[PDB]
Amino acid sequence: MGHHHHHHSHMSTPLTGKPGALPANLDDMKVAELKQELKLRSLPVSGTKTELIERLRAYQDQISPVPGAPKAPAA
Image (cartoon, rainbow, N blue to C red; front, side):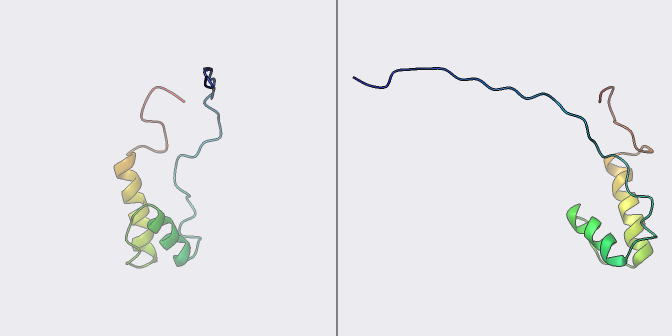
């Protein structure tokens, strides 16, 4: 005699609330903030303020060479 029973359920719908293009106020922020954005994206936090800013743009240019848009016909 044992606990013989079977039943399982689950559901999950794709929601909205989405990012996209990088912050255009990189120059307006602090060097530390740029180094923060870099480290989280596996980027080196070495160079000067302008270097870090343009390195963020260079990263974007690789992962998505567009002005901020989904690289596929979808949401």
